[PDB]
Amino acid sequence: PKLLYCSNGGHFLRILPDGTVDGTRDRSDQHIQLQLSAESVGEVYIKSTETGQYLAMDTDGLLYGSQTPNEECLFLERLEENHYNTYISKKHAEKNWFVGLKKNGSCKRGPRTHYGQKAILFLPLPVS
Image (cartoon, rainbow, N blue to C red):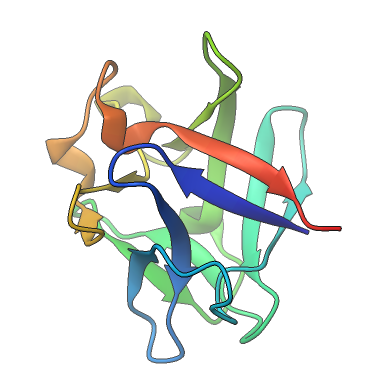
């Protein structure tokens, strides 16, 4: 069980009850506890422990909470220099579409992301 803290804006990734995805600075928020599960090595599912929803990216590059674990829900987890991870959509990997947060905490669409961006860097923080 983890938190994913984005160093752009300093937000924890949050999947809202209505399917929305964004970031919240508030560590006591109940929709930021996430469970990561692996299929292949380096391939993960990211699941809201509160609502049981899965993080997902659609075919136009945006993040939604999915009620179903489908192939839009697999991400490639990659360590980068300095301990943070990037999460690349497996289905759209060839387009370099990363899970991302803007500075103001709102989601970043897949086609508007790229390596080097602060928005794409997440620190996984194992919940006690």
